[PDB]
Amino acid sequence: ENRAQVAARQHNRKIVEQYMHTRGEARLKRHLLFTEDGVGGLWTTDSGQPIAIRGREKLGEHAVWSLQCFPDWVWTDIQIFETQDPNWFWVECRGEGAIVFPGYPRGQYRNHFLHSFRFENGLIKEQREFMNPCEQFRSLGIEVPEVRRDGLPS
Amino acid sequence: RAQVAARQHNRKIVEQYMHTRGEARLKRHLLFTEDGVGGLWTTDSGQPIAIRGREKLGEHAVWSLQCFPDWVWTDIQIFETQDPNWFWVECRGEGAIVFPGYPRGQYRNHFLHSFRFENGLIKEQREFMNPCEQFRSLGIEVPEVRRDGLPS
Ligand SMILES: O=C(c1ccc(Cl)cc1)c1c(-c2ccc(O)cc2)sc2ccccc12
Ligand SMILES: O=C(c1ccc(Cl)cc1)c1c(-c2ccc(O)cc2)sc2ccccc12
Image (tube, rainbow over all chains, first blue to last red; front, side, top):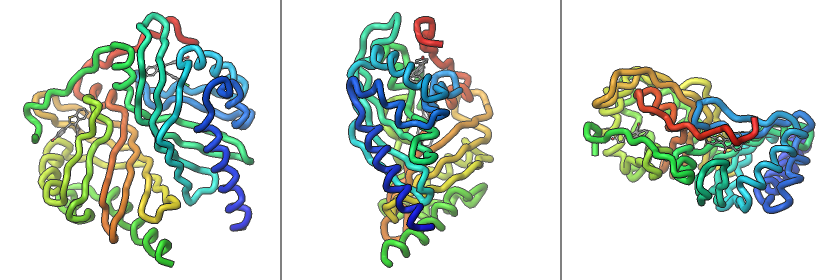
């Protein structure tokens, strides 16, 4: 049993590494790292609800959009965490690139990210991304509200 | 042996931290090293708000019990890692928010916590969430990214 779990964790780690280092035109094939019904997307949004892309095929189609709106995106400072579940990994990293959203000025986006990767049979079943949307607001020229700090300890 | 022993003890401390509620929050700083750091890494400013030192952490807990008087963490999932001294926690949290100068409200959010250990106690705790939900709980307007040109 431990041999099978050990093997799964070593294999899944290699897929996480591959995912995190995928840049440029290779992003068009990142969806092959997922199960046929795998889900990926952004769990921290302006609205409160995740924006998730469901299915390997739709993930490949979303990649076409991503190469237009995040044309040169890179993940940096990658730290991969194995867990007691051989099929569950977390990643702490940063990310950076141009942001080219419709109807907004071209900007430069930088942020800190946490990723969750859950695996089934050697491929990604669920990827979720967590960040602070305030930095994406700033990259688009959108005003970020401020919590008044006068009454807080300081 | 040395790594295994550390991880089992450290997991107990993470569990204790995440289940500390009510007046026991006033003693939660005793789970940290003398120079331990805790705080919020996802803010409105872009910089962390970190509380530095076990003594300042205990002082901050007094403020926290006033402003989050009934706070609980829920849906707690603790992740050990290949570092026996590094743990991650996925959870939710909820309770009243009583912030200076804002209407009393109810705050609910999803959280990730990072716990790094030194010699049996927490050296660094970091909390990550979506500040837009805290804005909502305070009655602060959340900006909206225009979707019109985005796939839907
Ligand atoms: O970057 C993103 C985003 C969301 C989900 C994914 Cl999978 C990737 C980027 C965001 C939006 C988006 C929605 C639909 C769409 O097809 C493309 C982008 S809307 C919004 C709002 C706030 C923060 C981030 C985003
Ligand atoms: O809840 C918090 C917060 C920040 C740090 C900790 Cl340790 C706990 C709560 C926030 C602020 C705060 C700053 C100083 C202070 O002594 C008390 C609160 S300012 C702000 C801004 C946006 C989101 C959350 C917070």
